[PDB]
Amino acid sequence: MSNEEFTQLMLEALDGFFLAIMTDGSIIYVSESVTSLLEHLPSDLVDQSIFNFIPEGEHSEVYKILSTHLLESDSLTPEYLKSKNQLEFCCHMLRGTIDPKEPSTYEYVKFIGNFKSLNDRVCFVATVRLATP
């Protein structure tokens, strides 16, 4: 069993995909299953902001809850960061469209992730799954 096969099965069982953002929400990575869960290609997401896909009324609380969580690191110097434990939150994400005449549709999803320094930058690596409220 390959690395890629294992993550296929785990993310299938979760109904989820992998996502990595910078602290301003800029998207640097998305795994292939976002297509069957949201009908975006990963390349439509990478280099865009996560907030381009979150309804505006949610932005304040998502950023607040991420910021507040990052403050739990004792220092913010990237070499010495390490998330103490996982962050959890839910929100909507816009779906892709074959028909732009159609009105916009959204999936309610749950994030689970951690801050982690790259390479030094601070990024949030997460699993995003379908959820219900």
Image: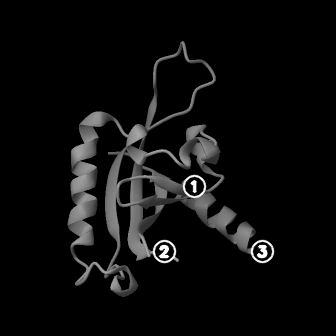
Judged by depth in the image, the label closer to the viewer, 2 or 1, is: 2
Nearest the viewer among 108 and 42 is 42
Q: Is residue 44 above or below residue 79?
A: above
Badge 3 marks a residue whose secondary structure is loop
Q: Is residue 10 above or below residue 74?
A: above
Which residue is depicted at the point 63% across and 51% down? Answer: 33
Residue at the spot of label 2: 118
- Colour mode of the rendering: one colour
Residue at the spot of label 1: 30
Q: How far apart in space, not on screen, are marks 1 and 3 (Cα)? A: 19 Å
In this rendering, would 125 be left or right of 43? left
Residue 77 in the image, given as x and y percentages of width and height: 31, 81
Name, please, the residue furthest toward the bottom: 80
Badge 2: residue crowd in 10 Å (few <14, some 14–19, many ≥20): few
Residue at the spot of label 3: 2
Q: Which amino acid does the dot numbered 3 rest on?
A: Ser
Is the C-beta separation of discs 2 and 1 under 8 Å? Answer: no
Q: Which amino acid does the dot numbered 1 rest on?
A: Val
Q: Which amino acid does the dot numbered 2 rest on?
A: Leu
Which residue is depicted at the point 44% across and 52% down? Answer: 26
Q: How far apart in space, not on screen, are marks 2 and 1 (Cα)? A: 16 Å
Q: Is residue 118 above or below residue 24?
A: below
In this rendering, would 97 be left or right of 93? right
Badge 1: residue crowd in 10 Å (few <14, some 14–19, many ≥20): many
Judged by depth in the image, the label closer to the viewer, 2 or 3, is: 2
In this rendering, would 32 be left or right of 78? right
Q: How far apart in space, not on screen, are marks 2 and 3 (Cα)? A: 25 Å
